[PDB]
Image 1 (tube, each protein chain N blue to C red):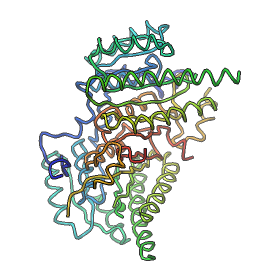
Image 2 (cartoon, helix red, strand yellow):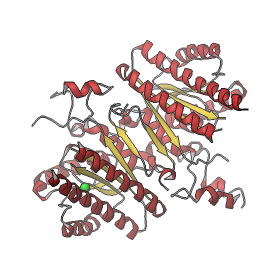
Image 3 (tube, each protein chain N blue to C red):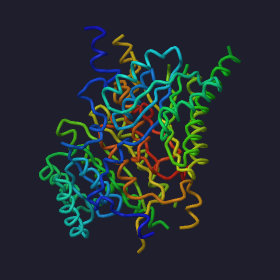
Length: 250
Length: 251
Ligand SMILES: [Cl-]
């Protein structure tokens, strides 16, 4: 055993082995996790994508969204055959986040992935800091559970809706960079998704001339990128960002 | 607007997010295909359902021929070997014809440049770059001639200021292509690999000391990213880069 150690832990051609399957790397069978902002377009689509790929998922959003979370979770549980549950939490409330940690463990079993899907005078600077601490503490309990259960996982941070988004975006990105460096050894990856203009419904012509694809993204085009980053397909990807913006930045 | 941008595709029971990652019905090619990244990326695309041409130098014809068989057998798609010296525009012209003849069209390409006395270093780099640029070019010429979209993926890997110079040029090229070809339904992206193993135990932990994951990547860990960028899973992704480096850039 001198060279045949490097050959055991570093195959050059996994695809040669009949038991290797590239598509199974995008599967979430056996995996459990949660999605914040889950009553919204990005969150519930990401959650449905993970559930259809085989994960158990907790849908997390504000207590005021309970009935929507409960209906979405029943619908996904039925359509995809996994345990999708609803867990209300206002993550700016410390006690509720502590309770969420308990209920994730007690109702899911463990946490393998978290999609921390954050929503965006001197009032703005106060509310930016409040919502960032909410994001931070939610990611924190996610990786505490991972560590406490002795396994790895995947954290995915995003922010969606000018100075406020830019400052929030920069903060989250630096936050994910440090997590990626500090938790890599616990098997925990951290990445961000930076969405461009995504359709969300009425409640144009100018901003689409900016976008080289000349259209908006849909919620499912973010959801497929979340599945990549949450799945083993992205097992060597940490500390980075995926821009999903139709070319906006280019 | 109503019907153009659906909000919850998952509510259709004949929709699946996992079909986005399939390459069934797709055809394309991979350069540097005898090397680690290229053959692993070819095998990923073929396993996912694509017909694939393996392109590399004429000196690799036998390797490519065996690789094409290995993958045709394992995955049931048409995988072929096409040698080409891509610094020769005549050969690249013939490569374009052979691709259209033997595959039917090109939907994706993984342009996988290798790296690699002052005048000579700059000349070597620019010849290498230009080989990448023109194989990229025949790919989107074929897409546009045949009236459909596609996906281009560019990477440079070791085969350091020469590597850095090559990486910056390819990134600019892909940014330009992504802007220019979006109208034609053609995406272009890059992959930036970190330390990937392709064949001393303390010299091991030596360079891993600045990799947070404290291990080398493996060729399959780049292949799966190639598959993500080639498939409809990344349909709103263009003009950007995916770094696959085990945390190297955030140490
Ligand atoms: Cl959050």
